[PDB]
Length: 180
Image (cartoon, rainbow, N blue to C red; front, side, top):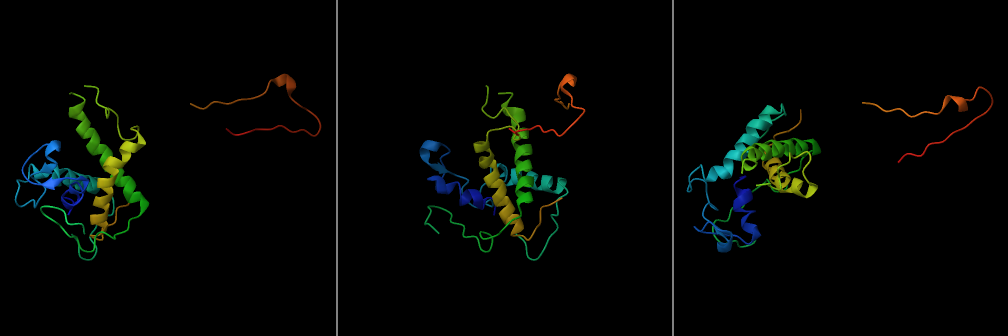
């Protein structure tokens, strides 16, 4: 179902099903059932989500089960998900998923930094806001499938003062401060 956000999401970006692994082909062989292509190359999809789930378990979030749990004519395989697309979510869960995106992007960063000055040298907390969305979207879809499983996902100092000479020991007085 998360592979569906790849078999019915990455395909939406002009991509087509079929065996030719290059952007010029506008096509990708694994854009199909995980039962067909091996679950290593398909682990490029399912496995990182699985680590995202082990990590969602690691967060102490209320992942405990509730209830039952689990269109333009695109070429190739055409998944048609039932009652998951409408699913709503509390804001904190997006933060947890964003943390998961941080952890995965950084564990990814252990190798890329070894290879030049990659644009994403940085941890997710300090990376540019436009790059938040790239992982945050895939994270939020995971939030959609999981909440559609009925799952929940929740758990120096400066000082500035006047000269003593100006101090006032008598009378009505008043001073002012603007906050930047």
